[PDB]
Structure formats: structure tokens, C-alpha cells
Image (tube, coloured by chain):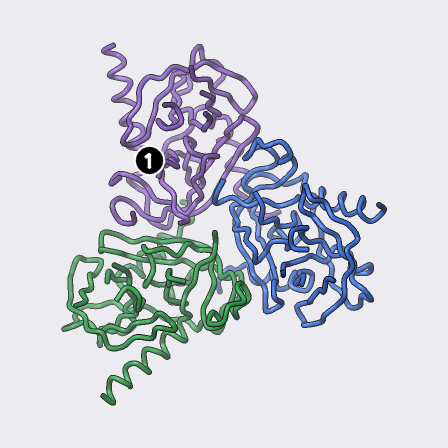
Chain colours: A purple, B blue, C green
Amino acid sequence: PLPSLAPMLEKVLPAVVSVRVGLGSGVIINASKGYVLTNNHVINKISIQLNDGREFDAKLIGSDDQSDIALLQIQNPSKLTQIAIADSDKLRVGDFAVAVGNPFGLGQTATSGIVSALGRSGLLENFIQTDASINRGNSGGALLNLNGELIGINTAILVGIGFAIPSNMARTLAQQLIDFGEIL
Amino acid sequence: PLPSLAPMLEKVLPAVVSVRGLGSGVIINASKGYVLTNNHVIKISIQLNDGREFDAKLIGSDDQSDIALLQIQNPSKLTQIAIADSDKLRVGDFAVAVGNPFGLGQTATSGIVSALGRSGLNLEGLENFIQTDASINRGNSGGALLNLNGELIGINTAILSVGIGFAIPSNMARTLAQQLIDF
Amino acid sequence: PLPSLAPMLEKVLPAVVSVLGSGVIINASKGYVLTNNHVIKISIQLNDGREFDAKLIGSDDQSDIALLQIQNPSKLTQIAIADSDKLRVGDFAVAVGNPFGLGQTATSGIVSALGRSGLNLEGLENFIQTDASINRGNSGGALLNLNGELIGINTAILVGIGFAIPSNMARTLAQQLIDFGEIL
């Protein structure tokens, strides 16, 4: 028996979705409400594709151009698996990170590495740095720890170093976008 | 005592060769002297780790998969690689990409199996092809993609998003070698 | 409890300095700091925010190595140095930096190639190859093993193609630069 990242990647698989509008990935944050976190540049009609092949309509709740974060609500949700979210403030340089995606809907894409830099100490301000490859194949998807908990959302808009939006900020700006949509 | 990838890399070292306009190659059949390499890389000469030089004949290639089969002229004391079932591969499995160009020594990159088939790139023809975040460059192209046991899972191809590398899976390269051996 | 590279990175943090580039404290008492000749009035900034003046002792253009002496040193932490002759392709490597003292930058990987094995270019016979990303953010800094001991000095001036001056050579050139500046 060989060590692998496949046993934790399989439990996370249904929470990571394909986004068709023009492709990218997304993450199910709330299954009951069908709230999916993805990237603004990916969407500038939206459809979401699960791992099991199921297709759903999705409406843009709102976005933040500066963080490249966009919140989507799937139209009539059912049998959805949501991701566990971790406190990104507890992240340390050297922690292991896995960047997961599912574009085209044909299967999971994963890259591995470490948390390289936090804050203004690398190369934006609020962003997370990782040596795990962030490309068009996992952009919009999840950045997880070895427990399979969301520590950030990958963004390819900006060497071997990648950017992710920390989960705490991704959660807060989703709440602010939900609240605004509730005044509307 | 530190954990390292060098112990498994030392047992695999004689099976990875220097294809001499240079590159790497893998000994699949010790007795017959069958060496798997890339088409773009390729008179042909092969150089072992121990410095031994051998003549090699081209017995067939596939432009689409960028694979090429070579047979070592007058083989002797050859170490072949163990081959693994690439169908049993899962995204997240650890991968090590080894090479030996110029014959000066072993080159290795580390990573994981990133995507299988058309999952990472939906381009027609990309089916079966394994994806890895282990760097695939001119220094290990033609060489072996290995698991933590040192068994061949793929043949490294430095052809094509950025940060991801492509390799021919072991089942596909073994079943292409069989076709090239006959016709 | 998750495995991480953060527990070893925290003990090594004070030995890596801000120089724009990085540098490594080799002798705490004398304040000798190893950095890249290409990044070189010089000021050094510690992790704790302390800023010191530094004088150029000497440099080696061929190895891209420069040795600096901290003017009036105090409470310095030096790095443990490992025998780079004992390195093997496949050994794990961590490339650490701290440009502008704002925080630690780290990349992870393996020792990829040694004796000019990766690129048949004259002059690379003395250097180390790594698949750990070597960029402007860790160039001048330390290449470490899993024990937190120096195995090399990152040099970005020369895909997983990163270069580092091995620790044995970097130590030797420092003594030779000390001795020379003594005869003068």
C-alpha cells in the first residue's frame, strides 16, 4: 500500500463543479441553498455540471472584481454535496496545499504544493501564494488542506507561483453578496 | 534519518538510458534490448548509466503519441524496468519523472498524477494521456514516469496549460510497442 | 493534527534576512551574511524588524556569491550548515526567502540534478538543480533540507529548473573572501 492524495480527493469530488457560460471550475459552499463560489473573469446564461454528469441552471447573485470572486445560486437544487471550510487565518507558510478542479465535467484535476507566502510578502494584498500550479484547469476551483477543507479559491488572472483568495474572505464576501441580494 | 526519493531512484537508475540531438529512453525488455523513447528526439546510439555505449535500430514510431521503439544491437547485462498497470492510476497518486540525458547522471522531478485522459484538456486525441504537475522538460523527455515503487506508469513527453506535463500511460505504450514489433 | 513544513520553517526564520533580495546568516558572532552577487550602500533587515548596515567583504561573479558583514551585530541567529557532498538526486529541498522582512517565502521540491546532468552547459558543474521554484522572492536565500540545515544558496539569474550554489562551495568561497580581505 502506497501513500496517495487520492483518498482525500475522492470525498471532496462532488463539491467541485464545472461552470459553462467560457469554462472554469466552482465550489459548492451551501448545498441546501445551492450556493457555488467561482471566478469573476470566468463569467464576464450560466450552467453548472456536477461530477455525476447532472446539469443545472445558475444565476449570478453578484461579484467582486478586485478579489475575482463570484457567487452563483443553482436553479432548483437536489442531492448536492457541500465542502467543509477551514479558517484561512490559521494558515502557515509551509502547510501543504492541493488545488482541485473539474473543467469540461470529464473529471477531476489536481495540483499539489505548499502555502508559499501570505499577505504582502511575495508579489493584491489579501491574496494567498502557493507553488501548486494554478492554471485554467483549476481556476475557480478549491484550494484545500490535507483534510479536504477549503482554505482558498484558485484564480489564474495573475514563475511557479499561484494565487488563491483565502476562504475567510471568500465566505465574508459571499455573505455581503447574499445580504445585498436580500435587499433586492 | 531523513525521508528521500533517492533510495527508490537508485534501483531504477540502470533501466533509464541516454538516447544520442539527445534525450532519454527506458529499457522495457532486458533480453531483447527494447528501449522506449520519444519520436521528436529521433544512426542512433544508446548510453547506459555505467558508461557502456550500444548501437540501436529504429523498429517503428507513432507521430500522434510521440512514441518510438528501439532495439539495442548485441545486448548484454541489461536491467529492465518493472511496469505497473496504468489503469489502476488515480488523480492524486505520486509521480516521479526520471531522465539521464548526455549520460552524465540522473535527472528527476516530483509531483502527482494531475488528470487522466481528456479531463484536463478536452482536445480530440488527448484521450488516455496522463497529466502530471511533475516538471516534464528536455531533461527527462523520453524517460520514465514512476510511482513510489519505481514501476513505470508512463513515458515522459515534452509536448502539449502551463505547470502541467503530459506522459503516455504504461498500458498504452506497451500495447503500441507490441503493434510496432509485428508491423 | 496535519503534517506540515511550517514546524521546521519557524526555527530557521531568524537566520534568513532581507538584503532587492534575501541572504543567510552563516556566522552570528561576526555577522557574516551570504547573498547573491547580482542583488548587490547595503542594508539588511531581520525578521523582527531590526535594520543594520552591511559592508561588502567580497564577491564571486562565477558562483554568484557575495559575503557581507553586519555592522555592529547583536542577538543574531545563524543557520546550521549541511554537507552538500552527501546530497543525492531525490532528496527533498525547501527554498526559503524573506524579501523586505514582511514575511517568509518558501517553495518545496526535490534535488533534481547535480554534476551538469540536467543541462550540458559549461559552468553548471559546480551548481545544484531543484524543481523547487527559484524566483526573485527567495534568490539569495537558503536552500534547506527537512532538518532546516543549509544545502545551498538560491540563485535565480541562471518549469522545474532552479539553481543553487551548494553549501560546501558557498562556505569555502566565504573563507577565501575573508582571508583575501585580510591580506589587504
Percent of width and height locating residue A21: 44, 20
In this rendering, position of residue C133 left or right of residue C52 = right
Q: In the rendered image, which quarter is residue A57 located in?
A: top left
Tell me the residue at 65%/44% (across/down): B168
**Chain designation of label 1:** A
Percent of width and height locating residue A79: 49, 16
Can residue C72 be seen in this snapshot?
yes
| C75 versus A20 height, above or below | below
**In the displayed image of the protein, which residue is found farthest to the bottom?**
C183
Q: Report which residue position mark 1 lands on.
A: A165
In this rendering, position of residue C68 left or right of residue B180 = left
**In the displayed image of the protein, which residue is found farthest to the right?**
B182
Report the quarter where the C terminus of chain B lies: top right
| A113 versus A85 height, above or below | below
Percent of width and height locating residue A177: 27, 20
Q: Is C98 or A40 nearer to us in this picture?
A: A40
Tell me the residue at 54%/67% (across/down): C120
Can residue B17 be seen in this snapshot?
no
- Numbered disc total: 1
| C58 versus C129 height, above or below | below
In this rendering, position of residue A60 left or right of residue A120 = right
Q: Residues within 10 Å of mark 1 (few under 14, many from 20)?
A: many
Tell me the residue at 71%/56% (across/down): B81
Secondary structure under tag 1 reads strand
Q: Is B156 or C106 nearer to us in this picture?
A: B156
Q: Is A132 or C134 nearer to us in this picture?
A: C134
Q: In the rendered image, which quarter is residue C61 located in?
A: bottom left
